[PDB]
Length: 146
Length: 146
Image (cartoon, rainbow over all chains, first blue to last red; front, side, top):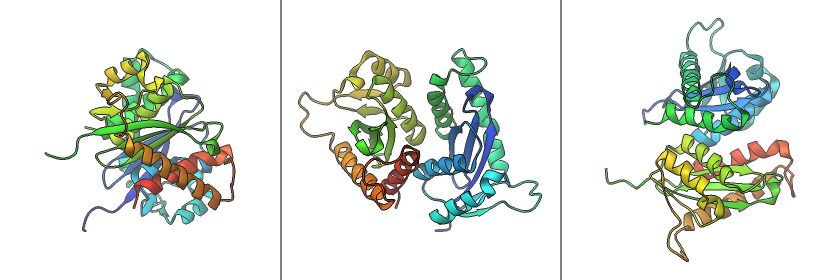
């Protein structure tokens, strides 16, 4: 069973077309390149935990999650949340440089699919709050399934 | 490629522990037995479409979806939503009898995992609104992943 390790890269990226819940939490399973995305009104430790609870239910529990040093990922609260689940976590190497690259690339693809799909429906600025959920779901389906 | 057909069974089931958003929309992919669950305040055609947009993003697009004749699945609105996506749909045979059985079984397992997990955390009645999301996510992770 010499298959890829069950390792995720998670990050937040802001997206004004999804306001008021413009902070998008994106997780890339580096074993499969699957992407999981959720929306949030504020970047807090808890928004990070809610994001991962959903990712877990969708991709299964990982062995480890790799994030940057944003404070929502390094607070005591998230440390304990992750210890509870049995998930290892690392912020990488001080002044990483690279190694968060799949997630940084995923954030950019994700934001361009949102924009091309939004504009396809006639929304050139903020998308109406009522259309957001389905539109986010649609972008995620597009980036995972072929 | 003589593998199972990409067919889903979807239904709604009420769950007072998740109030106010007590209507749980459950979809079983009959090819893999994967389950996808979302919560809603009201059973409407739209809640059905939002449920499926999420299922799609998680399990990919199915060839066909099998439901009962609840009105939220047979309104013009859902018909058009499904035509838009290219998804076939059937309410089965008049007075079906059986054939919605995986989804009926999934609804019952799902409701017992919610109850045993809720009670594990000390909530013997309604679960606090703030804990629901993670608790639903947790039940879904438990029923899909082993």
